[PDB]
Length: 298
Length: 296
Ligand SMILES: O=c1cc(-c2ccccc2)oc2cc(O)c(O)c(O)c12
Image (cartoon, rainbow over all chains, first blue to last red; front, side):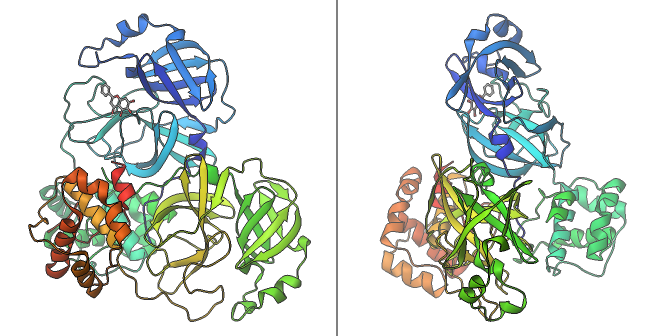
């Protein structure tokens, strides 16, 4: 009844191409006359903490990159490195280029991922940027260069390009300027992310979504202080709630009729006692990948 | 890393339009020179208690249906009824019509929904045809005509068109021939879905997925016949397992080394004793197919 939804992916699907350098093939994003892809496509198996990407790329030519848009092949007439991305300039300008921008999303925010393989889209799902700057996504081999995005109006805000899977199985990538999210580097060495936490602002948004959907069982008559709640949050590996967070939830406090500090009391009770086998909005776990904005849209 | 994934929606977005008739607008599906939409578009709020569609349809002309594909308007050149669907022959053939079929989805199978409002795609989600022929979808006021679909290769198998919410909160609709899923009718009436049952095939697939992910407390060394398993399942309102279901679980069984009937013996104990968490939750997921699982 209330479920994760992904943006319609059509404006992105039209931008997906396949980029091959040597014996390596991944996905790239074709916008106007530029193709973006992860730079480790030049990289053989010297990915193993060896890569000097400046050295590997100086030895390449436009000729060494093969880019296919569906059936058609596009001629690479230029190339450059932007952080951990390749910028391939091509002769044809994507007729399907949408209105778009590049944005760097902040932890806790959500976006849709179009999981791609050899340049053909295969799946779409919603997810979130974790506090430790990883995403708990679904990426197989060949998904590299898949992009994450939000759509507002006719405009596509790209926020993520996929680069690698970490040992723990979470995923790491960059924005569309090629700067990584988090402490990661694009080399096949072992890398740990920071210890993750739970997105408090999103759980509270979700609890509001349950109230707005006719699920009030977890509420109570109590209340707590911002700091008094925050003390419970730390004991449970939850992100401290900022005063601004409260201000973000204002509109939802209104429609629900529950004061933000009251919902914290409810949440504090849920964390301490558990859920006793009941469910909220259909889930038996405190759900932290809907934003206030997401809940408003449904 | 197990998430519900929807198919890419773009091959379907290219086909969504806006049908208006009177003061009622909903969504329509535009393939070639025909536009498909729910026939209840021609009803008034009054004529919703016991409508005679053939009557209401005879009392309408081409010029009675407004079909808008974005800013452009399409001209209705013809119109007929196909069961619970209106077929509007249109001015133009859709330049963006993909390779497609009309398939009839079986209970337990899944599909992607493109939730549209005013012909404008809003969002994509995945869901399953429940055994009681409803779906637990996400459809607000204005979603009728939104379409459900699967993609295999470059081809869109259309399988659902949305028509109604039932008082349960769940949703009912037709295939793209206009034949409803279930016993439901496009009249405001006292219809309601039957008792739902759990899709046992998908729960068994979920258990294989959890085993693959390192969760395996629920296994046991007991065994069960198909027949003794099916008898227990039905007492708990789980679908009985068919011969074909057992085969569809073949790949997952071998990948795990857990024989199908051994996983059934584990599910049997969970049904009779309860749970403890599986893949993070205490309720068994039943909308993840065996196919969803093998993809990872
Ligand atoms: O997960 C991936 C990781 C890497 C990689 C290479 C060097 C250092 C770190 C990661 O390359 C890839 C290339 C692909 O075509 C693909 O589908 C992938 O999933 C990966």
